[PDB]
Length: 557
Image 1 (cartoon, helix red, strand yellow):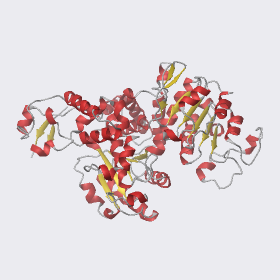
Image 2 (cartoon, helix red, strand yellow):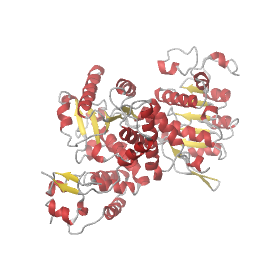
Image 3 (cartoon, helix red, strand yellow):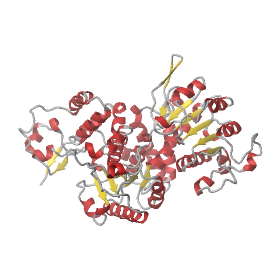
Image 4 (cartoon, helix red, strand yellow):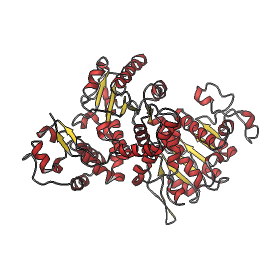
């Protein structure tokens, strides 16, 4: 790798976190960049720096303190921060990101030390070009943007949303190899309806309720246009917007700028990937299985739609695929004759003629009565109501299905329709379990059963690395499906015949690189990236994969 040419020197250099090498600056670099005497004499390696940093990390006693310490290192030496993270991925990922980052966002205005990222408030709405011009990076390739309205089970956190993009981009870098020189976290501050923040004397954001719908969509459009002018090929990822906004924005912009929404699209993809692999481990394939959803909101229907696309890819007709899926809201079941259904749920309603077979009747047909009459292979929970997967509901399902697949996906752990410990009991260790939130490996009869988590970090970093390596101009449904299918190929339970359904975090870089290949190939096949040989695309993936090592520096004027 060639030298990097850099204008900064002296204490400015030591204080520029992307470029600072601290004690690893060589003797020659210390001479050329006017650093002699500003540092202790010792020249150390990054691995020696990361080892001191790990010793420091271990002296902190709470999660939030570990989080602050990691952000402090990130703000001192970015390469060192990534080296340390790579050495302790399992321990730190939950400190960098969910669930600890949520606490950080709640308390943003109290724990604030310094600024990272770009803040675009309503008052700045006519100067977004000037703001983007203030970013010093020569090139930006991935932006994560939030308005902070819906943070992971905490609601509206106003400008404190910033911690989400920052954490998310650290995962792009650590998991997908996107260089931290090419990422940019952005918060849109259009107000907050959290009255406790509006009333917090320490609040650092715009002290105003959220702007109106018309005001909002004009403001976001100025933002999208400003981002396009400066970085036309950027990948823009939307994160933690309100449900009323998340889908419309995705539809409006997914063909105008290369973009996706991880909460909608990434969550569907990792879940479908898990379902593919689970079904193969239970014997057979997802197209064979019958499926009931508890939770028929926008999120449940979006995941259902992707399962249906996938089972079509496995051999079924659309009619057949949709017939194998049953969606349950508060009331018993979505069917024909149900009044006042919004367009997306209509697509999934059951027709009563197919239900002439059923033993019960009613306007309202309970979940226990749906489970009874379908006899599913897969039960999925997305509603968020606790205990709904009652012992009777589980046994009735195990009463016909030998190797049940059950997935309480509801977040956080408090809102799960059943715990892993419960359902593994109620199925005598026959069930396959994957969760939305992390659980510890379950103990049962001296036997240990690890519980896989449908973590989005299995999907988005590969997506980003694929986009950038192929130069893809948009992110198609088919590119997302290729990510799900590729992820399933790395299932340890299927590969070795034993383990979790999803792969271990030790392998997340390997998975991301494979996903990137598939996503890139799909893009080229669909005509949203230039065609190249498979060997060339692989080489691009390798050339774009940043690892935590220092570059050599040369000084310019």
